[PDB]
Length: 324
Image (cartoon, rainbow, N blue to C red; front, top):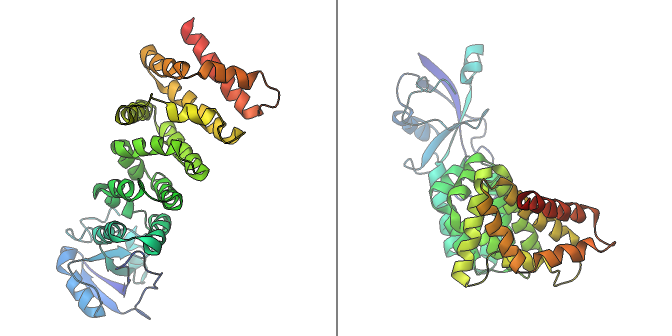
C-alpha cells in the first residue's frame, strides 16, 4: 500500500567532522509508496529537504532502529526489517537522509592516506568513536581494504598513532564482521605480533590483548596466529616466537602483567591445536630460546605473582600430558 513518513537530513559527509543534529528543524512529511523501489523515490526526499548532499551518495536510514534501507527494493520487499509500528498506530515513522556507508568509508580512507602531523593524529584518534557510533561502517571498512590502510598508515608511525590504530582495531573486533575481516587479513595478525617487539609498553600490552581476543574467538584462529608468527620470522630472519620470549625476559624490569598476557596467549594458542605436531612446533621453538629455564626461574621464586605462577604451571602441565 501507500505509506506516510517523516524525513530529516543528517550531515555525515565528513566522518571526522563534529557531531551534527538531524538537520531538519521540525522535520517535513512525505508520502512514499510501499510497492515501488526506494531508489526511485529518494529524489523526492532529497528535493523535499533541499539537502546539501549529492543524490548519488545519499541513503535512507530509519531513526528508531538505525537500519539502512536497501535502496533497490521497495519498503515492503524488505518489511522483514517492526517498522510499521508507528504507521500502524496513526503515527508517522521518521527517516533520515545521509551519506551512504560506502562514501563515508572512502572518505575515512582518503583522510588517513593523505594526512600527516596533528591532522593524522587527530583522525586516527577519532577512528574508535567513528566505528563505535556507526557499526554498519565496519563491514564496509573491511570490504574496502580498510585494514591494509591501517597497517600502511601505522607500520612506521609514532607509538601514539599505532596505539590509536590498535584502539580502533579493537573496537572493530567487537563486531562479527570486524573479526571475520581480521581473520581474513593475515597482515593484521602479522603486524600485531610485530608490535609485540615494540619499545612502547602501551602498544605491546594492547597488541597482546588483541591477539588474545583473536585466539579466543575461535579455535580456528590459533593456527592463523601461528602462521602469522612464522611469516614474520621468515621476513625478518628471526626465530619464530622471539618477540614473545623477549617479553618474558623482562628486559625493562619486573612486569608480571605482560607476562600473564604473554603466557596466557601461548597456552591458549597451544590449547586450540588439533595435532601434537603443531603443538611441538611451537613448544620446541620456545624451548630452543630458553623457555624451560624461564619457567623455572619464575617458579623457583616466591615473589612471583599468583596469576603468572598459575599460567606457568598450566604451561608446564600441558607439556607433561603430551610427552607422556
